[PDB]
Amino acid sequence: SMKRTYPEPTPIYHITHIDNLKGILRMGKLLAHNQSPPKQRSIAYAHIQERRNRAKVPQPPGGVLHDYVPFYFCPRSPMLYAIYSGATEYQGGQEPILHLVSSAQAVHKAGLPFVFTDRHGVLSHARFFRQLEELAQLDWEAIQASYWADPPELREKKQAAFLVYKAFPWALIEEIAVYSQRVGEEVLKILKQFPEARRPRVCIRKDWYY
Ligand SMILES: [Cl-]
Image (cartoon, rainbow, N blue to C red; front, side, top):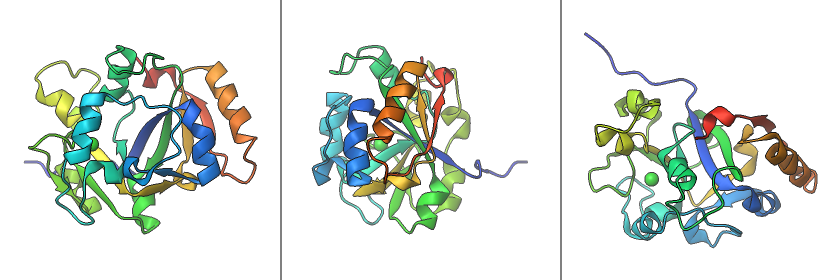
């Protein structure tokens, strides 16, 4: 006899190459793929990339996954694993990859349109939601899983996504997590070039990486 719950607050994580940070700070936002972002560096699995151009979103404001900025509900994501494993076109590995941390509740409180899924949003079987209470429908056991090799559904459910329409404001980022001290020190040197950008905490979290 159990009732489905979810973590409150609900952290959300977006991974990006450090080379993109200057563009984000200058714009004050992360732009969705389809909004012509000032992206320096793709870390994008090309087979996922093409699929996000045509993966339809059934909750308003609708469109395709490339109309949204994607966050996952865990660090040390399967997409990060693809970067670590060299499976992406991008061959620089995980050390230059930042985790940008926010929360689902912060996006709602800011009044920004969002949708979220219970599994990788390119899957035809993905379910989509737009109310925070429906976070209970996700498989938190999979999302939080350190063991996700088998069954095959674990990799899929662990890629549950929090999708923010068109743009994600920089000032909703509470933490930049990094692989190493040397990357953290480079992040602080970039933040200081944009003294009017919010300066979130910068944290070394080698345990969020493979
Ligand atoms: Cl997705």
